[PDB]
Amino acid sequence: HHHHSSGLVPRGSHMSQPSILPKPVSYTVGSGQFVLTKNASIFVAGNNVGETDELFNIGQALAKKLNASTGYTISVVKSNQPTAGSIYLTTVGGNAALGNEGYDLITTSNQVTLTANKPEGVFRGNQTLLQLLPAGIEKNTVVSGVQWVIPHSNISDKPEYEYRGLMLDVARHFFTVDEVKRQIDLASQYKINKFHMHLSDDQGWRIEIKSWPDLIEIGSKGQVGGGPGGYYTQEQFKDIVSYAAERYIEVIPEIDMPGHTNAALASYGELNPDGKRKAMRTDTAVGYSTLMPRAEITYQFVEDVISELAAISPSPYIHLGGDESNATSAADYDYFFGRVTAIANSYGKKVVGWDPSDTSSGATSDSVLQNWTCSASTGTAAKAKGMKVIVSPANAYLDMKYYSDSPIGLQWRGFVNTNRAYNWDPTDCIKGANIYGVESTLWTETFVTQDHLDYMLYPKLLSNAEVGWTARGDRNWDDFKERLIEHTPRLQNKGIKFFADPIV
Ligand SMILES: CC(=O)N[C@H]1/C(=N/OC(=O)Nc2ccccc2)O[C@H](CO)[C@@H](O)[C@@H]1O
């Protein structure tokens, strides 16, 4: 038998017909079609009144999306007696084998029925439903001249990995609450279920801490290249969390420590050995900054920050960073990370950290390693301690240029085009681990505008999202590539300023 790898498409990028991404466990199509008309309602039915009420909110979110493009006014009904032309969302009789996020979605001529185990699974199923309707459905304004049809079809689905996330760096360049909500919204449509916020680094501090107000008054006032920066009040952070919760997306806030701390060090002189504030940094160097690992003021600071963040962040996880502490000795890093893990745990939070944080003698088996290095020795500690691992290999570093000539992006992990972002498995990063899942990281050294985010995340994130959701045995670049071509108008319709990758 003959085999080959993909080259660039001759003559440039290529960028009744459903376009499901990520690929579901099974999808069959039969004869006939359902027609969504102006008289459609969404019916919801759970196993008890509380569950029905949650399904009602989900139904309303779906109706809002459908109404924007159809111009209809579909409303939602608490009833288990759907009428012909209805969409029906239910958790009654869900297939347990499909888990919390799984669903069956069966479309007949008279009715769409989505059956899940939990409301979360109805929400994930709804993302598929939107992809079964014609391109045009994802428009934010009314589309005319398109019959809103769904082929008679049968889908069963569930994720391969529990953790399927996106990180946005808002420290290097700041993005508004609206901009952050948009990226959360867009990612949710591809079944991303985790959003990691990199809230602080050398060039800026982005979260209001009432007990240390100069973190904002001084530490938020810049960014890479010297713009004005910005920050989130605690009320704004809560709003982001709430918006994410409506999409069954867990928000994990990161305060990076003991390295990548210049913004805090520039805000408070007492955090520095010489008692003087550091100058703010607007360059892109990494590795040089450190908290004082043997000063109690350091641990008081971390505790105040953790206390306030814990109060407003319902996720059971807090990310404490731990990458590139090149100005911290191995012994002091071990000690430091153990102390801050104890603080986090006392405030009811489990710690996530970049490698090599798993090597801290103060880590517990409840701690989580974010494995970005992906070397043979990375996560040896995590594995021995029974710590879950989230992988972020080169293929998940979405800030990497697509090609040598990309006008934005970095290249320290090589170039990562749409194909590279697809052709990998989490076990390529680490073997012998309990892999919790995958996280796409969008660092923002070189990204200033919303269009820059769109360009780098789309289509790269679609590739990563399928690696997280679809089983390895069912992943195939030739298949995905052709599906991606088909999906292109949907990206256009959503207003995503994607890169038309020539490998697609
Ligand atoms: C965990 C992580 O990725 N840390 C830093 C980081 N790690 O940086 C490198 O080590 N870059 C580098 C390594 C060797 C040679 C040249 C650059 O990469 C990101 C950008 O992709 C930065 O935004 C992060 O702060």
Image (cartoon, rainbow, N blue to C red):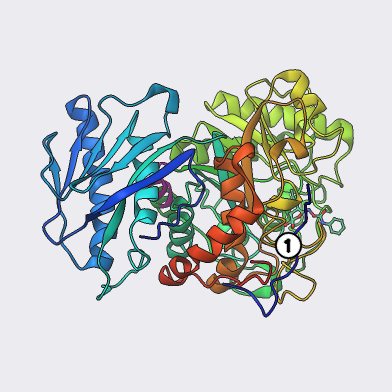
Q: Amino acid at mark 1?
A: Met
Residue behind label 1 places its C-beta within 8 angstroms of ligand 1? yes
Residue ranking furthest to the front: 1
Region in magenta? 240-248
Count all numbered tags in the image, as a single digit.
1
Instruction: Give the image location of residue 359, x and y in percent.
Output: 80, 28
Q: Position of residue 25 (x, y in %)?
A: 49, 38
Which residue is tagged 1? 400
Ligand 1's image quarter is bottom right
**Spot occupied by residue 397 in the image (x, y as percentages of width and height):** 70, 54
Q: Dominant secondary structure of the magenta stretch?
A: helix
* Crowding at mark 1 (Cα within 10 Å: few <14, some 14-19, many 20+): many
Give the side of residue 268 with respect to residue 155, left or right: right
| SS at mark 1 in the image | loop
Of 12 and 338, which appears nearest the observer? 12
**Residue at the image position 17 percent from the left and 64 percent from the top:** 72
Q: Is residue 214 visible?
A: no
Residue 4 coordinates in the image, percent (x, y): 78, 56
Residue 442: quarter of image:
bottom right
Q: Is residue 358 magenta?
A: no
Q: Is residue 245 magenta?
A: yes
> In terms of image quadrants, where is residue 461?
bottom right
Q: In the displayed structure, would residue 117 be above or below residue 164?
A: above
Quadrant containing the C terminus in the rendered view: bottom right
